[PDB]
Image 1 (spheres, rainbow, N blue to C red):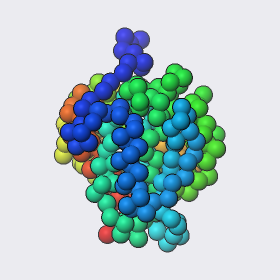
Image 2: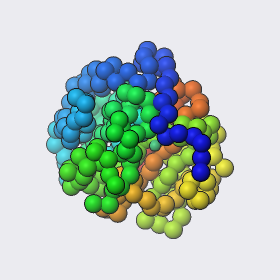
Image 3: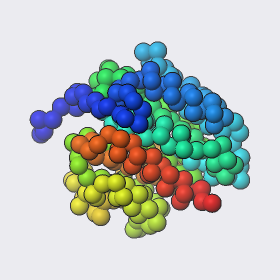
Image 4: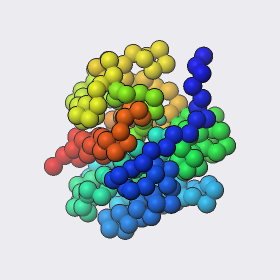
Length: 262
Ligand code: NI
């Protein structure tokens, strides 16, 4: 038993974005500018409280190119993820899409994001229950399971934060005994920004990696469903917000470098 409430709200100022971290209208406005510029096609998977839960993809998936998914914003206190993706998108040109079918799920929990807390506004954890209790958002994602499995065949990265942490770590899944270059490259990217953590649910973190720990999360679901490689980065929430934005963007850049190399 712990005294730290999952219902607690957390908010930061961003100098990169010149707004507060829970400024969901600004988020959607900036995101839309980037997806327009990059020629990405919006697929709305659902909506709650007037906020769309969108998947963005290339106008066409090419069979010869790897298919990668990056997701974030399952937990509303973990705001560096969705803003990290926006920072990442700002850095990209359309040429990236000639070598990879990149899919983006920037913000799964907009009601939690708006209020700066982990749950949606109905008290549910959107990153639990995937096997197929799920949250409303989880159910809407599961209505598009086949589309999401297609999108993540060659790899999935989820960008989380551990709000009370000062150190960083990564969860990883590979079809091997021991972590390889995929896992260690991600760890190293995160490690440029923060000190590595040296337990999650009785499971030890070893050299900043938690390896092949299956639970009912979206990422474990996609691995059981066939994704070749998966990771969940965890930036420390007790550190500087704009540095967390930078670190998330850097994890994403490394994921793409490993999985869709030049
Ligand atoms: Ni999280």
